[PDB]
Image (cartoon, rainbow, N blue to C red; front, side, top):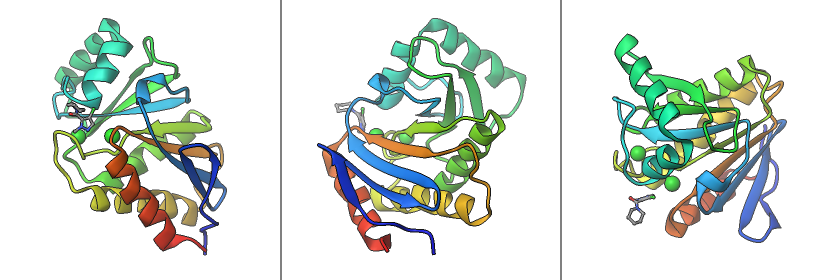
Length: 182
Ligand SMILES: Cn1ncc(Cl)c1C(=O)N1CCCCC1
Ligand SMILES: [Cl-]
Ligand SMILES: [Cl-]
């Protein structure tokens, strides 16, 4: 109903269409990417500095760390939106790694439409300190994008890329894409 064909447009990058969105996966350091939004997978206190969250907070800088702690004390947040600091993005969206991954991705997509953004880059949310299983995480990320497209909600969002630290996790995402392909 929505899925195109899986191919490789560049070395180490794999892609397929999901409605009007191009969905891509690759392995690398997410802090070197450029996108309108970069997603951080963190703790419910928004101050985890371990694995991909360490890299994101160190690169983003102390003003972003300060933004995170200020918002965390103000209210009970499922996720937080901050500036990009010294990352190459307009905003960072900090999601809780232990939360339902489909719900977290749905929220990121809706916030990006609100800002008329076109590109998103995310890690394999929940596979680090939260220790969620990689194929459940891949299934949830892709399901969220399918639902967003099915509801007619994709207008400004055109590109969603997962940059994955461990090559063995990339292999799981590629197999999930092949399961779905048209
Ligand atoms: C499990 N994991 N997924 C992404 C990242 Cl980053 C990590 C991580 O904790 N590290 C630190 C130890 C050396 C390998 C990378
Ligand atoms: Cl995590
Ligand atoms: Cl990752």
